[PDB]
Image (spheres, grey):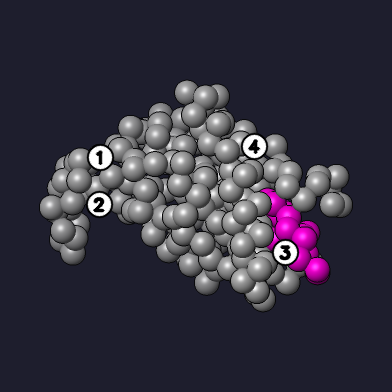
Amino acid sequence: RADGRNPNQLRPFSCTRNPLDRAHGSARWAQGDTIVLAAVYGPKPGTRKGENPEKASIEVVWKPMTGQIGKQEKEYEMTLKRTLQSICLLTVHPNTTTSVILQVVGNDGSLLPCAINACCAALVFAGIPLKHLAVAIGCGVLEDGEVILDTNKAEEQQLKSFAHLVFPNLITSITHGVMSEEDYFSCIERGLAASSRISDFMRTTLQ
């Protein structure tokens, strides 16, 4: 690949443990130049009037690195909320609201998978009960089916197929552009065997 990685290679990731003093848990998560800040606010008593108070609430606001949220970063906001509500164990702290704020710092590709991983780390740090870890990976599909892991901004302007996969340690998957069923399986096959690198990071280094 242009940047010198091979197809199954994840760009180097990193994380500063809770930069924010006011947050119960936070994570500035970086993969290459794509960097994100995730802030979580412990479980807070009470439930939005339009929610169920019988189960715990998870809420999310996606904030652009500048200006205000466009049609793309607001579907990301949506996917992220689906994914987080999914992995969180909701039966532990009923009548409670956990608010996640995601602030984009840089965007060199795989922004939604990055924001996902960032948020999984911050939840863990805030002591929010999870069913399992969420490990997300942006997969790109090359001309004749060659699968690429953790695409950047440049590869995202080149390829015609790709998938956002998130594995439990699937959870959710969203594909963009042409995707044969063979392409799709290569992506899940490839992503899965790579994902253990991200969760080994969450399970050891980040604790």
| Residue that appears at 43% across and 63% down | 78
Q: Secondary structure at mark 1?
A: loop
Q: Which residues are magenta?
A: 140-155
Which of the numbered marks, if any, corresponds to residue 57?
Answer: 2
Q: Are marks 4 and 3 in contact (CB under 8 Å)?
A: no
**Mark with earlier residue (4, 3):** 4
Q: Which residue is mark 1?
A: 43
Looking at the picture, which amino acid does disc 1 mark? Pro
Residue 141, percent from left and from top: 72, 64
Looking at the picture, which amino acid does disc 3 mark? Val
Residue nearest the viewer, comparing 126 with 86? 86
| Residue that appears at 51% across and 62% down | 173
Q: Are marks 2 and 4 in contact (CB under 8 Å)?
A: no
Q: Which residue is mark 3?
A: 141
Rounded to the nearest whole Å, what is the CA distance between mark 4 and mark 3? 22 Å
Q: Which residue is mark 4?
A: 13
Residue 10 among those drawn in magenta:
no
**Mark with earlier residue (4, 1):** 4
